[PDB]
Amino acid sequence: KQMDKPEWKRVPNSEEDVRKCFGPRSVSRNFGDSDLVQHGVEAKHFPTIAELLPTQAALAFGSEITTKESGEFVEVTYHYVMKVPKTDKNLPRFLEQVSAYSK
Amino acid sequence: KQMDKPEWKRVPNSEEDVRKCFGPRSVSRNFGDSDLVQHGVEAKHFPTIAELLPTQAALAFGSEITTKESGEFVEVTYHYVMKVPKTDKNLPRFLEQVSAYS
């Protein structure tokens, strides 16, 4: 069903993985190791990683949001910044996911 | 409470509003009209606006994420871009929220 939803409402899993939902890892979409890419939210360590992912409301009210018309679409850009304490136990495994494809 | 959570896990409501959870509206935090600011996710039209907000997984796997060390913290930046069809019924109300404070 994920691929029947708009891209921004997709929740990847083992059936419909990250590759199928959001395409291959790149400079534009750089988050997720092989495990997360293949199993999405069903990945073993995803719950640990998700501790440093903002909520839907936090994204809305904590981001700089800009829009511009692009063909038959309105392109919405979110710029969100969050500071995580270096002592955070979930931070190491999260950082390993950042540009994991290039590591 | 929401103020007992890290800022990125806060879900504002009528008790702990957007201003309390994420501070005043500004050029850096520009989303939300007076109704959304005062009632957060309890705002009457928040569900309509929420139709154009990405899921936590979509944000994770669809964003350009960059990190930088800052003192005793690691600053995590998310750059997410989504293309909404101009026909989307939720888009007009969503656009009214962008820089509503100004």
Image (spheres, coloured by chain):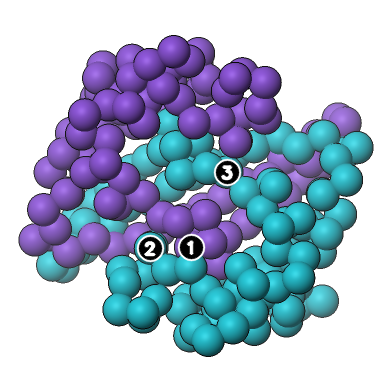
Chain colours: A cyan, B purple
Q: Is residue B68 visible in the rendered structure shown here?
A: yes
Q: Is residue A30 visible in the rendered structure shown here?
A: no
The answer to whether residue B85 is left or right of residue B75 is: left
The residue tagged 2 is A9
The residue tagged 1 is B58
Report whether mark 3 lies on the same chain as mark 2. yes
Write down the chain letter for disc 2.
A
Query: With respect to residue A87, does A52 lie above or below?
Result: below
Residue shown at 28% from the left, 51% from the top: B51
Residue shown at 64% from the left, 37% from the top: A82
Q: Amino acid at mark 2?
A: Lys
Give the quadrant of residue B75. Answer: top right
Residue shown at 52% from the left, 54% from the top: B56
Q: Count the labels in the image.
A: 3
Could you say whether the residue bearing mark 2 is in a helix, strand or loop? helix
Q: Amino acid at mark 3?
A: Pro
Considering only order in the chain, which callout, 2 or 3, is on the residue closer to the N terminus?
2
Q: CA distance from mark 3 to mark 2?
A: 15 Å
Could you say whether the residue bearing mark 1 is in a helix, strand or loop? helix
Write down the chain letter for disc 1.
B
Q: CA distance from mark 1 to mark 3?
A: 11 Å
Badge 1 vs badge 2, beta-carbon distance below 8 Å: yes
Report whether mark 1 lies on the same chain as mark 2. no
The residue tagged 3 is A54
Quadrant housing the C terminus of chain A? bottom right
